[PDB]
Amino acid sequence: QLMEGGPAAVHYQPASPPRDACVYSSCYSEENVWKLCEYIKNHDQYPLEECYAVFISNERKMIPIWKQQARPGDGPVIWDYHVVLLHVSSGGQSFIYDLDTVLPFPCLFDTYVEDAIKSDDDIHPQFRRKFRVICADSYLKNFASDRSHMKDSSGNWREPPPPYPCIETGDSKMNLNDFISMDPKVGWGAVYTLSEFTHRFGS
């Protein structure tokens, strides 16, 4: 036997509705996460400052993620980028909200990293993952997307858009590339390698 040794969030109450009740569009995870942040802001259950949008990508925009609903089974989906929500609960236990995972929604941080992300040690280097972590308040204040990246060469949708107007701010109608970028000189928040990300938020 081994006992864990920071309070355990055994009675943790999710910060969002159940997965099937959440606003969701396939291939628009940046907006699915934005909508979760907006729910948390308006629900008055948790401080928004406990939550973060997390972009996952790399220089070549090819990242594997396992346990994804788009590819049932034991193989990864290779995304250009993917976005999830991280809630660092007040006791310190972190939870990941990924509407696209087959893992629980929400899922304990360490389990998500173990099963969905996996180690980068034996991964071919051009596939290794980096993480941009943005405070949910900053994400709501600053993110904008005009969805122009989701059109084919003739201007028609590659995947159907979410059923509400494009997210825009007073400052921008499109800055999605500044969140997908893993250059720390660009954009908002902090950029971590996988080992830095797990060191920062893991148990």
Image (cartoon, rainbow, N blue to C red):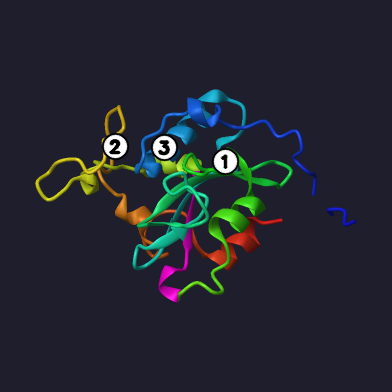
In magenta segment, residue 155: no
The residue positioned 30% from the left and 55% from the top of the image is 177
User: Between marks 3 and 1, how big is the CA–CA gap?
Assistant: 18 Å
Q: Is residue 59 above or below residue 8?
A: below
Give the residue type that dot 2 points to. Answer: Glu
Which of the numbered marks, if any, corresponds to residue 49?
A: 1
Q: What residue occupies the far left of the structure in this picture?
A: 154
Magenta residues span 125-135
Q: Which residue is mark 3?
A: 32
Give the residue type that dot 1 points to. Answer: Glu
- Mark sitting earlier along the chain (3/1): 3
- Mark sitting earlier along the chain (2/3): 3
Mark 1 crowdedness (10 Å alpha carbons): few <14, some 14-19, many ≥20: few
Q: Which residue is mark 2?
A: 168
Q: What residue occupies the far front of the structure in this picture?
A: 73
Mark 2 crowdedness (10 Å alpha carbons): few <14, some 14-19, many ≥20: some
Mark 2 or 3, closer to the camera: 3
In the image shown, does 115 or 71 lie closer to the viewer? 71
